[PDB]
Amino acid sequence: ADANEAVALSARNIPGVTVVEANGINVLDVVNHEKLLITKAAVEKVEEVLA
Amino acid sequence: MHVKKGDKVMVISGKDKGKQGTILAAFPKKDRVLVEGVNMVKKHSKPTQANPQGGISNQEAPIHVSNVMPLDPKTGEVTRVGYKVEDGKKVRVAKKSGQVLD
Amino acid sequence: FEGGQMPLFQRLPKRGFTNINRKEYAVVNLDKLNGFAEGTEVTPELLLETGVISKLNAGVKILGNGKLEKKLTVKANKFSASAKEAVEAAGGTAEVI
RNA sequence: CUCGGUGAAAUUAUAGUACCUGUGAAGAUGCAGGUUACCCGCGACAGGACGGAAAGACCCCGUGGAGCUUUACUGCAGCCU
RNA sequence: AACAGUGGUAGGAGAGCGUUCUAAGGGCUGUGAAGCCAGACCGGAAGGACUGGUGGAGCGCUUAGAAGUGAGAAUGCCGGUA
RNA sequence: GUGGGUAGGGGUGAAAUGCCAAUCGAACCUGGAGAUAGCUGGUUCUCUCCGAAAUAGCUUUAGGGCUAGCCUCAAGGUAAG
RNA sequence: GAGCUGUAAGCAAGCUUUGAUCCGGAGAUUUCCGAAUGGGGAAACCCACCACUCGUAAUGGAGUGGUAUCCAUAUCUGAAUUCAUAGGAUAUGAGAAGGCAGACCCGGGGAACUGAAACAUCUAAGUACCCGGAGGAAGAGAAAGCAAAUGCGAUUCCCUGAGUAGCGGCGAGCGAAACGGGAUCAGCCCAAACCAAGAGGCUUGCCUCUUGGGGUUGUAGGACACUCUGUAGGAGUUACAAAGGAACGAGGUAGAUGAAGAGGUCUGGAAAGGCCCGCCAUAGGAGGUAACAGCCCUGUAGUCAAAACUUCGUUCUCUCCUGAGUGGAUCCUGAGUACGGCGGAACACGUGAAAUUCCGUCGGAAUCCGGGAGGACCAUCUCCCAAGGCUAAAUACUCCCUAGUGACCGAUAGUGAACCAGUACCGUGAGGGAAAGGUGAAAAGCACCCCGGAAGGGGAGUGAAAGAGAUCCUGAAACCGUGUGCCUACAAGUAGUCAGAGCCCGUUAACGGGUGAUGGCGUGCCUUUUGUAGAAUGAACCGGCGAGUUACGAUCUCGUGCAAGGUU
Ligand SMILES: [K+]
Ligand SMILES: [K+]
Ligand SMILES: [K+]
Ligand SMILES: [K+]
Ligand SMILES: [K+]
Ligand SMILES: [K+]
Ligand SMILES: [K+]
Ligand SMILES: [K+]
Ligand SMILES: [K+]
Ligand SMILES: [K+]
Ligand SMILES: [K+]
Ligand SMILES: [K+]
Ligand SMILES: [K+]
Ligand SMILES: [K+]
Ligand SMILES: [K+]
Ligand SMILES: [K+]
Ligand SMILES: [K+]
Ligand SMILES: [K+]
Ligand SMILES: [Mg+2]
Ligand SMILES: [Mg+2]
Ligand SMILES: [Mg+2]
Ligand SMILES: [Mg+2]
Ligand SMILES: [Mg+2]
Ligand SMILES: [Mg+2]
Ligand SMILES: [Mg+2]
Ligand SMILES: [Mg+2]
Ligand SMILES: [Mg+2]
Ligand SMILES: [Mg+2]
Ligand SMILES: [Mg+2]
Ligand SMILES: [Mg+2]
Ligand SMILES: [Mg+2]
Ligand SMILES: [Mg+2]
Ligand SMILES: [Mg+2]
Ligand SMILES: [Mg+2]
Ligand SMILES: [Mg+2]
Ligand SMILES: [Mg+2]
Ligand SMILES: [Mg+2]
Ligand SMILES: [Mg+2]
Ligand SMILES: [Mg+2]
Ligand SMILES: [Mg+2]
Ligand SMILES: [Mg+2]
Ligand SMILES: [Mg+2]
Ligand SMILES: [Mg+2]
Ligand SMILES: [Mg+2]
Ligand SMILES: [Mg+2]
Ligand SMILES: [Mg+2]
Ligand SMILES: [Mg+2]
Ligand SMILES: [Mg+2]
Ligand SMILES: [Mg+2]
Ligand SMILES: [Mg+2]
Ligand SMILES: [Mg+2]
Ligand SMILES: [Mg+2]
Ligand SMILES: [Mg+2]
Ligand SMILES: [Mg+2]
Ligand SMILES: [Mg+2]
Ligand SMILES: [Mg+2]
Ligand SMILES: [Mg+2]
Ligand SMILES: [Mg+2]
């Protein structure tokens, strides 16, 4: 939902695992990654903007 | 370099992989070392004044420094190199055990 | 260019002038006013906010194309004769502002 | 010119590259019909290859240029007032 | 299926081939990549494989994207050699 | 002979437009500059569908151009041709 | 922190844990030429004078420093000429000079080709170019503004307005601005009245000049008077006065530390590759390493580090400093100015209906009961207060330095230049201006033998490979050769094609391959043309390179989203 430092740092070095905020979601990142791991807070934040 | 003249090292790569030996000389500018008994070449020396007879001389040729690792003093196994400050002096230490290489 | 035949534009005369003080109004026909519910004071600010008109220009003129079946207090800069009739005919009040 | 030494060039679509009469962008080694001709050179000669050389100087065209002229046009310097 | 059509310059229209690079996916490759050489293979064309030799480290394929994307002529330019 | 002077819309000329670095009806170099070229040359893979024109009018126009004519593609009208 | 005395091998002689080489900060030295400056000169040379120093008995010789011009300031002399002044002399000056980054900026001067299908107004274009001046930016800037609202409030730049308004042989073309939306924001100091003090002309209580105070503007402000009020809180070296110091913090200019596999096994010259297993990861950036490495090395993430010089910020210090009201007696508020005529230029605006701005020339105001502007002009109204100055930021550009990036190049490309290139070479000169990358992982760079004067070669050895042996990866084509399966010395040839024996082969196995006696048919390719085998054009051959692109607008088709709305 917000900029999680620990998650962003922990995932940084794993190949093929990108971390974004809710506002930083984009078509290319969604389509390029197989799985989409969203938090409940982030889903609410996405639904705020898009819906 | 991570090794120096005088160090016993294991050759970890090349034809002489597995062979231990002392570094007879180091070449920091080329990142190469001369290890005793390792990478022998047959030089075809013509008759000079310095070498009067000539002939085919068997001599060590340098290998790349990244193909050798220093031995751990405890186990005798290869080790990566760390550094600690002891008595003011910096010393190389075996990362495997902990003990001082030099 | 017509290969040296006197070009069309140049054969024909210039006509008219441009008025420095020309007013163009944002026109609104009666069919657009049907969008609003009865009792709504249709001001230029409301028309612009709702997006019935995109820009104001000199002002809002109400014109008399289409039908009106809503009692509205239409407030506008200008009205056509038929528009002012049609607003008043269906219970409304055309007000020049 | 012959032998020994050394060794360029212009040119050149590929060529196993006859002659006659004809034909054809109207003057053909190369097309047609005939006539003649074993294969490869060397010394010579220039009739042809519309031979080579140089995107014809002539001529015309370009709303191309340049130099020159004058009572062409429009200007400017200088000079006079 | 039937019927009809399919010469073509300028030129309009359509469908494709191949080249380099990128993305994603999926592969190949020191048990030998690209390139090069050869062959009597395949496709309607552009073209594409397969096998062997040379070579000695890179390269296809699929889908999409982007172009310094294709040469036989320019008295073209540079090189080489007649 | 040596040392000097004159410089390009200029110099110099016992005058030929002669000469000014194998350049002269206006030197050479660099730049404006990829000047402009209605002119000539060239313009690179394939197959299929269709397929002209070399005419009229006007044009400082006549080997250029424009509009019309003739070709092509698409969408309509539909069945006028 | 263990090697080192560069390219660059090599012998030589040495240095270095008593810390070298090497890296960074600050110093020292720094020939001669060059602005070049003691004078001269054909740059890198020559010749001086004056001090002091070395040397000689002395001359000759040598060393160090000073000695250009202009300008500023001061002092001393002071011509014709009386006082003077000009001029001269001397001293003090981190005063100027010259260069460049082929960029950006502001000025002075300023083309033409070209476009207009000719051409002169016009365009190209105030471009190129030359010249002057800069600065890190410059220029502009605090309303004699924009405008026409119950307004705005310095300038600059971006979006938009708008290819509009307009200008225009009303041709070709040229082409705004304000409003609106943003970036950034900051305002000030004088001149004058007047006051005080001093100076020199006494013009003789007047005037002029120089310092300090005072003062700073528009439904006017200030002087001047009034009563207030401050003289140290506030401000500051980026304008608003101008120097300096300390401390603290964060950067820059060297560095330090830094996790995890030689895992096993398989090919192999070598393993970073395959297969089967681990592990680290705030580190799976990158480069290297004998083939492709997060775990081999140099590193990377993270965290640290500076004696010295340096940048920024902060705080203190330091330095500097009253700002409000009420009155209209007078006084002040930028003069050869504004403005006008004439001639030009600049304004998008070409003399036009031509405001506005600037230059030359001549004429020439008002001065608060005043002046300017609102696109001729007048009136009214509105807005403003010129003829003085300063001012950061947003903006432009990149010779450089540091870090990094690319559906950018990969040796005819990419810089002209991957290499000792602005070199070689060419030119009197300005100037023009190339070609030229690849042994190998490592020199292990072929001891030795043999032919040869050598070159070169054949062995041998090294290497994974020498047909990797020095313009040494690969190694196409033209072109040049050696060998020979088929054909060829009675033949008339765009060289093929179709028919076809004979002979020789044997494949991607196909109603195969090579050759071709003989028969039929048959005038290359391209360009340009009414028409070309053409006795029209172009190409010696082979290879490489070599031509509808991109940007911004317009329009149409197709596609997609939304739809009387769509879109920023
Ligand atoms: K002909
Ligand atoms: K002849
Ligand atoms: K191959
Ligand atoms: K050619
Ligand atoms: K000249
Ligand atoms: K002359
Ligand atoms: K010359
Ligand atoms: K049409
Ligand atoms: K002109
Ligand atoms: K023209
Ligand atoms: K290694
Ligand atoms: K004017
Ligand atoms: K004047
Ligand atoms: K105003
Ligand atoms: K070059
Ligand atoms: K042969
Ligand atoms: K035949
Ligand atoms: K000819
Ligand atoms: Mg490590
Ligand atoms: Mg001879
Ligand atoms: Mg014919
Ligand atoms: Mg005839
Ligand atoms: Mg004939
Ligand atoms: Mg015949
Ligand atoms: Mg001839
Ligand atoms: Mg000719
Ligand atoms: Mg057809
Ligand atoms: Mg047919
Ligand atoms: Mg087409
Ligand atoms: Mg490739
Ligand atoms: Mg193969
Ligand atoms: Mg190309
Ligand atoms: Mg001459
Ligand atoms: Mg030009
Ligand atoms: Mg037409
Ligand atoms: Mg013209
Ligand atoms: Mg400055
Ligand atoms: Mg400066
Ligand atoms: Mg400034
Ligand atoms: Mg200041
Ligand atoms: Mg480390
Ligand atoms: Mg292992
Ligand atoms: Mg290899
Ligand atoms: Mg004033
Ligand atoms: Mg007016
Ligand atoms: Mg190459
Ligand atoms: Mg090059
Ligand atoms: Mg020379
Ligand atoms: Mg080979
Ligand atoms: Mg290699
Ligand atoms: Mg080679
Ligand atoms: Mg015979
Ligand atoms: Mg016979
Ligand atoms: Mg003809
Ligand atoms: Mg001929
Ligand atoms: Mg011709
Ligand atoms: Mg020719
Ligand atoms: Mg060629």
Image: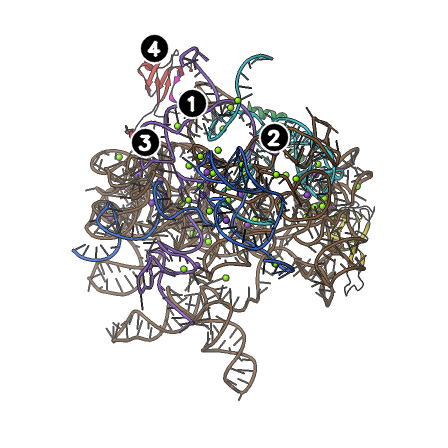
Chain colours: A green, B yellow, C red, D blue, E cyan, F purple, G brown
Q: Number of marks in the image?
A: 4
- Disc 4 marks which residue? C89
Q: Secondary structure at mark 3?
A: loop
**Chain identifier of the residue bearing label 3 in the image:** C
Which mark is first along the chain, 3 or 4? 3
> Label 2 sits on what residue type?
Asp
Q: Quadrant of residue D73?
A: top left
Q: Secondary structure at mark 1?
A: helix
CA–CA distance in space, label 1 to label 3: 49 Å
CA–CA distance in space, label 1 to label 2: 37 Å
CA–CA distance in space, label 1 to label 4: 27 Å
Q: Is residue G35 left or right of residue B46?
A: left
Q: Residues within 10 Å of mark 3 (few under 14, many from 20)?
A: few
The reply to whether the C-beta atoms of the residues labelled 3 and 2 are less than 8 Å apart is no
Q: Is residue F77 left or right of residue G386?
A: right
- Disc 3 marks which residue? C7
- Disc 1 marks which residue? C49
Q: Is residue B42 magenta?
A: no
CA–CA distance in space, label 4 to label 2: 60 Å
